[PDB]
Amino acid sequence: GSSGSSGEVDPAKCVLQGEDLHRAREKQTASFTLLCKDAAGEIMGRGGDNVQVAVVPKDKKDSPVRTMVQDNKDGTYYISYTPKEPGVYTVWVCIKEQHVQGSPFTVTVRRKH
Image (cartoon, rainbow, N blue to C red; front, side, top):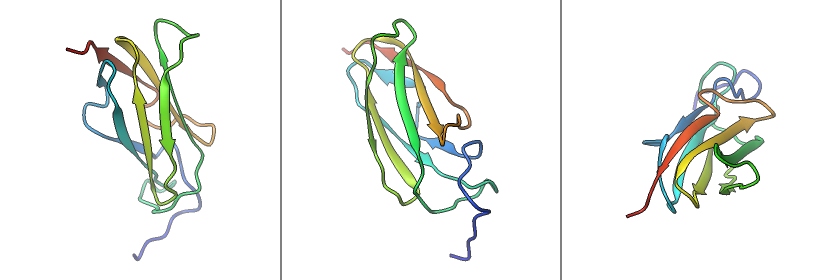
């Protein structure tokens, strides 16, 4: 659609999509969309990128967190994670060995009712 990327995807230009991305619930499945933009900071509408997703509790380090990643190769990635214990966590989102904008970030998980 009358579009033309600069050359490749840029992590510093990439962004995250989703409401209350910094708020999760204990034993809950939180998913968000990862938009891929080029060096021009515009939609590239392509895939073939290396996305790295990993969540770790700010409390412990040897205790990882369940995560999921379903590559689409269309322009939007599908990431999902579910905390096992309440508290604070650190979501790691980087592409091509590079931390994207507003990332990594923190996540305050609450206790289930």
